[PDB]
Image (cartoon, helix red, strand yellow):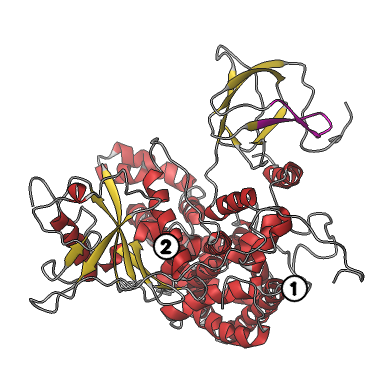
C-alpha cells in the first residue's frame, strides 16, 4: 500500500518459493524453500527426483512424522535461518518432555 | 629422540617454550577445561563461569579441549574442537574462546532429555526405540579422543 | 511405518526399492512420491529391530552394482565403434544418478560407518581389481572403487588404437562430434578410484600418449608433402591455419590439461625440425618487404 | 522489527514472516502469492476476533515480544464462498503421547524377585 514496496519482496511469490511437507496424518506444512534446505533429507528430495523437476512442483511425504513433531521441526527452521548470518542474541529453543523422544527421532532422521 | 612417533597420537609435546594464554568463556555453560598430558590422558582443571576468563601458563604444542562441566557436552575453542598454543608474538597473549557450538536439533534435544530423565528410565520413555541407544551414548571425552585420532590420521597426507 | 522401532521384512521392501533404484540409473523417470518413499524405506530398514537391515542392504547394493556396471561394460563393448557413444550416455545418466544416490543415502552414511575397519588393515584386498568385498567407506568413494576394474581388459589396446585412427585426421577423415569424443574422455578420468590427488594419471598414460605420437606422424607426412610440392610462401600460412584448427579441436575434444600437450607436439612437428630450411628462407624474407611473411615467421 | 507467524485453517499451516508495523491487509497479500486465491475472499482472525484493514498487526497484539521464531503467533483464516463468510474452524494437531515412567524422575525401587531377572 504505502511508500516504497516491491511485489517480489515481502516474501510473496509463486509456488517455487515455498515447499510443501505432508505429514503422516496428512496435515500440510508450507515453509519457505530456504527453511526446507536445512534438513538434508528434504534438501536431497528437492535436488531430485529430478530429471523432470523443472516444473515448479515440490513435495515431501512423511510416513513417520506426525504433525505435533513436524511443527517443532518447522519452528526450528524459522529460528535457524533467522539468527544465522547475524550477531544478534539467540535464546534457547523449547522442547516439551512428552514430545522429546519423537522430536529426537524425527530430528535424527531429518539430518538437521 | 627416537625414530617413529612414540606415544599416543593425541598428546601434548613437552615443548619447553612457554605460551601465555587466556581462556575466555563466551558460552552459557560452566566450562571444564581439559588438558591432555604427555601421556594423552585428559586432566581436569577448575571450572569457569559463563561470564569469566582466566590466565593460563601453557606451552606451545600443548593440547586442550573444553566441555560442559556438568554434561560433558562438547564446546568449541576458536571455533574448533582442540586448542593448541602457538608462540606468542607482539601479539601478546593467545586467546582461546570457548563458545557454544550450534548443536544439531537432534543432539540438543538429546541433551535436554538427558538432563530431565534418569538414565535408569531412558527405556521407559515412549519414544522411538533407536533413540534409546542414542540417549545412553552421552558425551564422552575419551570417545572424542578416539574420533580425533582417526580424523587426525586422515589429516596427515603427503606434502606437495 | 513409524520413528519408533518396528519389525520390517527385507525382501518385500528391497524388490520395490530395487525397481526404483534401477529406474534412476539409465535415466528412466522416477516419480516424486516414490523418491520420497525411498528415504523413508532406507530409514525403516536402518532402525528396525536390534539387528539392522542397514548392513544387509550395504552388502546387497555392493553386489548388485558390481554385477550391473560389469554387465553394462560387456553390453557397451559389443557395438562396433559405437562403444564410446553408449559409454558416454551411461556415464551421463550415471553422473546425475550417482549424485541422487549419495543424496538418498545421506542418513545411512551419517549414522552407520562412524568407523571403518579402523583397527586392522588388510593387505589381502583393498587396492586394485579383486572380487573381494570393497571398503566400508561412503557411497561416492565406493562408486569410484567399483569402476576402476572395467578398464584393464585386453580389448583396450586394439580399440583405443582404432578410435585414435579416426581422430588423428584433421582432413581426409572429418569429423567426430564434440559431444561423442568428450563423452569417452571424461569417463576415462572418472573411472579411477578415490585418490588423495588428481585422478588424471590413467587418462594420460592410456589415451594421451599413443594419441600424441600418431598425431605427430600425420603432421610429419603432411609437412614433408607440402614442403616438396609448394614453396615457402604458402607453407607458413597453411601451417599457421593447421595450428588454428588444432586449438579448436583440442578445446572441444579434450581435458584442459592436454589442450597444450596436443598443440605443443603439432607446433613442434611443423617448425622446429624444418627450422634449418626456414632460417635460410627468413634471410631473403627480411631482404624483401613482405609484412605478412615476417609476421607468420615471427 | 520482524514478527514470525503461522497462518492456519483446517490442517494446513503456512510459516511466514511479516513486519510488526505492517497492515493486516499486507499479510493477505502474502497468502495470495502462495495459495493463489484473492485477498478479498480471505478473513484473518486473532483469537476469533474479526480483523479489519484499518488495523495493523502490532496493534492486534502480534508484536515481537509474544511472536518468536521459536514459537509463533497463530492467525485464524477463513474463506468465503462469495459474500457469506465461512468463519473460523481449525482442526488441531494430534495430541503428544502419554509421558512414560522412564522420563519421570526417580522413585524408590522394589524388592528382588525370587527367580533370575528376564
Dots 1 and 2 on the same chain: no
Q: Which residue is mark 2?
A: A71
- C142 left or right of B14 in image: left
Work out whether D85 lies above or below C236. below
Residue C132 % position (x, y): 79, 72
Element on which disc 1 rests? loop
Q: Chain of mark 2?
A: A
Was residue D92 drawn as part of the magenta stretch in this picture? no
Query: Is residue C262 among what the camera can see?
Result: no
Using the image, tell me which numbered label, if any, was put on residue C51.
Answer: 1
The magenta stretch spans which residues?
Answer: B32-46
Residue D58 % position (x, y): 20, 47
Front position among marks 1 and 2? 2
Q: Kindly indicate the quadrant of the structure image that contains residue C208.
A: bottom right
C229 or B5, nearer to the observer: B5
- B37 left or right of C291 in image: right
Do labels 1 and 2 touch, CB within 8 Å?
no
Q: Chain of mark 1?
A: C
- C78 left or right of C298 in image: right
For label 1, the crowd category at 10 Å Cα-Cα, with few meaning under 14, some 14 to 19 and many 20 or more, is few
Work out whether B93 lies above or below B50. above
Q: Kindly indicate the quadrant of the structure image that contains residue C121.
A: bottom right
- The residue that appears at 66% across and 62% down in the rendered structure is D101
- The residue that appears at 74% across and 47% down in the rendered structure is B143
- The residue that appears at 88% across and 26% down in the rendered structure is B1
C167 or B100, nearer to the observer: B100
Element on which disc 2 rests? helix
Residue C294 % position (x, y): 31, 42
* Distance between the alpha carbons at the discs numbered 1 and 2: 31 Å
For label 2, the crowd category at 10 Å Cα-Cα, with few meaning under 14, some 14 to 19 and many 20 or more, is some
Was residue B38 drawn as part of the magenta stretch in this picture? yes
Amino acid at each position: 500500500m504505502d511508500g516504497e514496496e516491491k511485489t517480489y519482496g515481502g516474501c510473496e511469490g509463486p509456488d517455487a518459493m515455498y515447499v510443501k511437507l505432508i505429514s503422516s496424518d496428512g496435515h500440510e506444512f508450507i515453509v519457505k524453500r530456504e527453511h526446507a534446505l536445512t534438513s538434508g533429507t528434504i534438501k536431497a528430495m528437492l535436488s531430485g527426483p529430478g530429471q523432470f523437476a523443472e516444473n515448479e512442483t515440490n513435495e515431501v511425504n512423511f510416513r513417520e512424522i506426525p504433525s505435533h513433531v513436524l511443527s517443532k521441526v518447522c519452528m526450528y527452521f524459522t529460528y535457524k535461518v533467522r539468527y544465522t548470518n547475524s550477531s544478534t542474541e539467540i535464546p534457547e529453543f523449547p522442547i516439551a518432555p512428552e514430545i522429546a523422544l519423537e522430536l529426537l527421532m524425527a530430528a535424527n532422521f531429518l539430518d538437521c | 629422540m627416537e625414530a617413529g612417533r612414540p606415544r599416543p597420537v593425541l598428546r601434548s609435546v613437552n615443548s619447553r617454550e612457554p605460551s601465555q594464554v587466556i581462556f575466555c568463556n563466551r558460552s552459557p555453560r560452566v566450562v571444564l577445561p581439559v588438558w591432555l598430558n604427555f601421556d594423552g590422558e585428559p586432566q581436569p582443571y577448575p571450572t569457569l563461569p559463563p561470564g569469566t576468563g582466566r590466565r593460563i601458563h601453557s606451552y606451545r604444542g600443548h593440547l586442550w579441549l573444553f566441555r560442559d562441566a556438568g554434561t560433558h557436552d562438547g564446546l568449541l575453542v576458536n571455533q574448533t574442537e582442540l586448542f593448541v598454543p602457538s608462540l606468542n608474538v607482539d601479539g601478546q597473549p593467545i586467546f582461546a574462546n570457548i563458545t557454544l557450538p550450534v548443536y544439531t536439533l537432534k543432539e540438543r534435544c538429546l541433551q535436554v532429555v538427558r538432563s530431565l530423565v534418569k538414565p535408569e528410565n531412558y527405556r521407559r520413555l515412549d519414544i522411538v526405540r533407536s533413540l534409546y541407544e542414542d540417549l545412553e551414548d552421552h558425551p564422552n571425552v575419551q570417545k572424542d579422543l578416539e574420533r580425533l585420532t582417526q580424523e587426525r590420521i586422515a589429516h596427515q597426507r603427503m606434502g606437495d | 511405518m513409524s520413528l519408533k522401532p518396528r519389525v520390517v521384512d527385507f525382501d518385500e521392501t528391497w524388490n520395490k526399492l530395487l525397481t526404483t533404484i534401477k529406474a534412476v540409473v539409465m535415466l528412466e523417470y522416477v516419480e516424486r512420491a516414490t523418491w520420497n518413499d525411498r528415504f523413508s524405506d532406507i530409514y525403516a530398514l536402518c532402525v528396525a529391530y536390534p539387528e539392522p537391515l542397514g548392513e544387509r542392504l550395504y552388502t546387497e547394493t555392493k553386489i548388485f552394482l558390481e554385477n550391473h556396471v560389469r554387465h553394462l561394460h560387456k553390453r557397451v563393448l559389443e557395438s562396433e565403434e559405437q562403444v564410446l557413444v553408449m559409454y558416454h550416455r551411461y556415464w551421463e545418466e550415471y553422473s546425475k544418478g550417482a549424485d541422487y544416490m549419495d543424496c538418498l543415502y545421506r542418513y545411512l552414511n551419517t549414522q552407520f560407518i562412524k568407523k571403518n575397519k579402523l583397527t586392522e588393515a588388510d593387505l589381502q584386498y583393498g587396492y586394485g581389481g579383486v572380487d573381494m568385498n570393497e571398503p566400508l567407506m561412503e557411497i561416492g568413494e565406493l562408486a569410484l572403487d567399483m569402476w576402476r576394474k572395467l578398464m584393464v581388459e585386453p580389448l583396450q589396446a586394439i580399440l583405443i588404437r582404432m578410435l585414435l585412427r579416426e581422430i588423428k585426421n584433421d582432413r581426409g577423415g572429418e569429423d567426430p562430434n564434440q559431444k561423442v569424443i568428450h563423452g569417452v574422455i571424461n569417463s576415462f578420468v572418472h573411472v579411477e578410484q578415490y585418490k588423495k590427488k588428481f585422478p588424471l594419471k590413467f587418462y594420460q598414460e592410456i589415451f594421451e600418449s599413443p594419441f600424441l605420437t600418431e598425431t605427430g606422424e600425420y603432421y610429419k607426412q603432411e609437412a614433408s608433402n607440402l614442403l616438396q610440392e609448394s614453396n615457402c610462401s604458402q607453407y607458413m600460412e597453411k601451417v599457421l591455419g593447421r595450428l588454428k584448427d588444432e586449438e579448436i579441436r583440442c578445446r572441444k575434444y579434450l581435458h584442459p590439461s592436454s589442450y597444450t600437450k596436443v598443440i605443443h607436439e603439432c607446433q613442434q612437428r611443423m617448425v622446429a625440425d624444418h627450422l634449418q630450411f626456414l632460417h635460410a628462407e627468413c634471410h631473403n624474407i627480411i631482404r624483401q618487404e613482405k609484412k605478412n611473411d615476417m609476421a607468420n615467421m615471427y | 522489527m520482524d514478527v514470525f507467524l503461522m497462518i492456519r485453517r483446517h490442517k494446513t499451516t503456512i510459516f511466514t514472516d511479516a513486519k510488526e508495523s505492517s497492515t493486516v491487509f499486507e499479510l493477505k497479500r502474502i497468502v495470495e502469492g502462495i495459495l493463489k486465491r484473492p485477498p478479498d475472499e480471505q478473513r484473518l482472525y486473532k483469537d476469533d476476533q474479526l480483523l479489519d484493514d484499518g488495523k495493523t498487526l502490532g496493534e492486534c497484539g502480534f508484536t515481537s515480544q509474544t511472536a518468536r521464531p521459536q514459537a509463533p503467533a497463530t492467525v485464524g483464516l477463513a474463506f468465503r464462498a462469495d459474500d457469506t463468510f465461512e468463519a473460523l474452524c481449525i482442526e488441531p494437531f494430534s495430541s503428544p503421547p502419554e509421558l512414560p515412567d522412564v522420563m519421570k524422575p526417580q522413585d524408590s525401587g522394589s524388592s528382588a524377585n525370587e527367580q533370575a531377572v528376564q
